Amino acid sequence: GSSGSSGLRLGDRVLVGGTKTGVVRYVGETDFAKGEWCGVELDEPLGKNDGAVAGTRYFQCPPKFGLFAPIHKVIRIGSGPSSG
């Protein structure tokens, strides 16, 4: 469903899991799992990797910070078509 809330910009604060807030560092397909994944970087050491899959590093990040998760499994915090 290509409407608007999809893809996630490269550098936006998104929710991963439903509690851990992290900014998007990478967006696109991977070389391990089929489909499109999004590399979300957290503020605390609550990650699994540092944006490196089998040596393939899409984005430079410190150890235990970046967490690769499916795009559909990512929630956005920012709203574009909003006013308040």
Image (cartoon, helix red, strand yellow):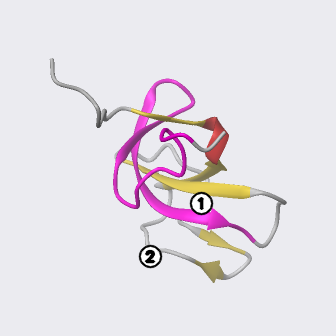
Please tell me which residue is depicted at 50% across the width and 43% down the height of the picture.
46
Quadrant where the C terminus lies? top left
On residue 20, which mark appears? none
On residue 60, which mark appears? 2
Q: Is residue 6 above or below residue 32?
A: above
Q: SS of the residue at dot 2?
A: loop
Q: Is residue 12 above or below residue 61?
A: above
Q: Residue furthest front?
A: 3
With 13 as the anchor, is 7 left or right in this view?
A: right
Give, as a single range, the part of the protein colored magenta. Answer: 3-30
Please tell me which residue is depicted at 43% across the width and 69% down the height of the picture.
61
On residue 49, which mark appears? 1
Q: SS of the residue at dot 1?
A: loop
Of residues 32 and 75, the one nearer the viewer is 75
With 63 as the anchor, is 71 left or right in this view?
A: right
Q: The disc labelled 1 sits on which kind of residue?
A: Asn
Q: The disc labelled 2 sits on which kind of residue?
A: Gln
Horizontal and vertical percent position of residue 24: 43, 54
Q: Is residue 48 above or below residue 3?
A: below
Q: CA distance from mark 1 to mark 2?
A: 11 Å
